[PDB]
Length: 448
Image 1 (tube, one colour):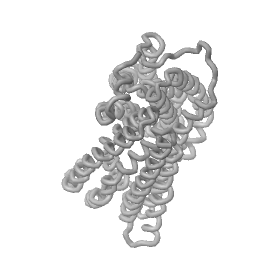
Image 2 (cartoon, one colour):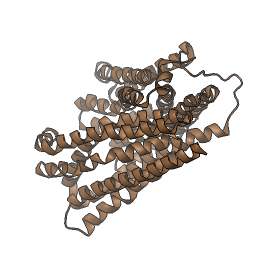
Image 3 (cartoon, rainbow, N blue to C red):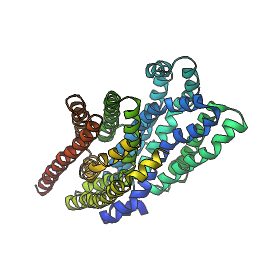
Image 4 (cartoon, rainbow, N blue to C red):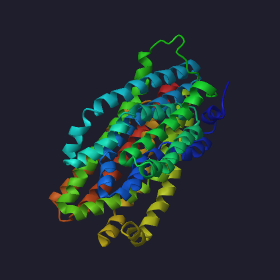
């Protein structure tokens, strides 16, 4: 008893990684565009309304981080079981994750709703700015469960190679919102709150497609039942050992971003911040083609770990590095060459931005070596290693090397670029060296 997705995981790893890359990426990224579309749609109401939608953005990404954290812990745990032919173990991870989604989502709602007012005022919102932002935040915080269920049900689909279905449901919600937004905001006059209800409604639609697949159609590989449900401490530890370190990695990067922005103010000021902001978003676009491949790699290395197949696993992740490396060489060449054209497009602080695009994106050619190693760590079930590596990349060597450059050096805001490049390049080398050690150990365990 199998499916098209299950055969994919148990088949050639290269075929699986390449086939999964696109839907993996899209099915895990379109969610980010809710806040973007809501903000653009309400801008016709004035800069006040645009600012209210955007104040919620880091709160919103934090919830995604936790939802998506549980998602990968779930997906990577199912993938291993399918590779292991542990049918009952996979059915069990899926039910455990669904109960966790209800617990985590509701806990988020009842913890944020009373806290959201104090949180906004700490950012700097005062008076009416808090009021309009809260009108928006209140709707979505009370739908936090929906966001978590979507990311976990999809983690179940991606756990068995069914990325297309996970991608579909997300795309339908993300697109409905673009159409729904102006109807609620303007045609019905619900304003900023209208944008929030349009986002909440679109997310529910995503829920209903996923729920139909899991609970009504049930054409999935795994079976979802509460019949003879016995809670498993060993299953919790398997999910959480990837999921929680995944959320914390996301936290570590946000903290890193905060300290890095502080240095770019010091250098600095509003101008250095505008430049750092523009350059960092471009360089992040340059990683976009590589994100999905690192997500497939986790599912594929996972299936090979469950099969106890150490060659299939090694072949899978080394191949992902290989493909990712060739792609990033083109990306940085594109940025190196066409920098003044790209600088112009994103400033349509110009010459300072050109100088930043010819420095910053250079670490991208080493990124895959540390990124795919980290994805492999998650595949074997060892998220804490990916977490450690992440902290080392961001809180120690990224922040630490930029602070010294700007406080002990003459480079100015440029020291922030150099510190990030060096910080990222060194970590990729250490991580990749670490992954090789981990590989050699797995080859010995498998022999003995």
